[PDB]
Image (tube, rainbow, N blue to C red; front, top):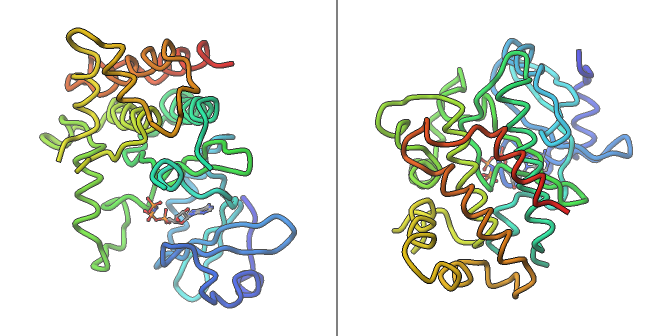
Length: 279
Ligand SMILES: Nc1ncnc2c1ncn2[C@@H]1O[C@H](COP(=O)(O)OP(=O)(O)NP(=O)(O)O)[C@@H](O)[C@H]1O
């Protein structure tokens, strides 16, 4: 039943939605009850979707405190994630090697829960650096896994950024989806592969137009792999990383970004890999 909220308490926490808003028009910061939160405004009663998706709770998934339906709109209150999104940090203090490995581990931990032990399993479909939030200890918190996906919303929209949805599509989406709409948990594995590549290189998923998911193959192929990998590594790490474990992590990302979905590993395997190379 989560926690039923009175719309009043939401107005006061958000200063009556007084450009206390985070970037997203529907995303506001609510300061109240000591622990801060984030309020997302959604059109129409989406209560039915919550009663299904509310099954998904995990330490590394953005937690839903509750919801409120007021005058034809649904206001959802999530745990506030200070330090914003991984994209902000990778494309802007800099995340150390330890932190980058921790974040990859939390995401693999959440993807492992979603694909196997969520009752029933659920495919994310929208795993991106911008959706992976961080908390005060820079731990991962997956977010836009439902109802915020482009065509998952029952109430369609025309306040839509086409060029932006398409940029993320080419950089994160697996080929079997772009070509046939084939939706399997392997598409999350492909996306998760690109995230790791972002964590290792800090590069844009689509650079200035080469995709970050095709460069890892050239970096690990042929000869002089050590030198090509050093150059691939994020400069901001400044040698403060074990090149051995970086190559290993880059290897598990290449398998994740393979074109054949059945060749890709299950996230459960990636979760076991990241846990053994962790501190
Ligand atoms: N629970 C939360 N805690 C803190 N910040 C949040 C939370 N949910 C969303 N945000 C912020 O709200 C913005 C994104 O809102 P969102 O509804 O996810 O749309 P979005 O634009 O698709 N996400 P993004 O990929 O980062 O641009 C980002 O600046 C996030 O940091």
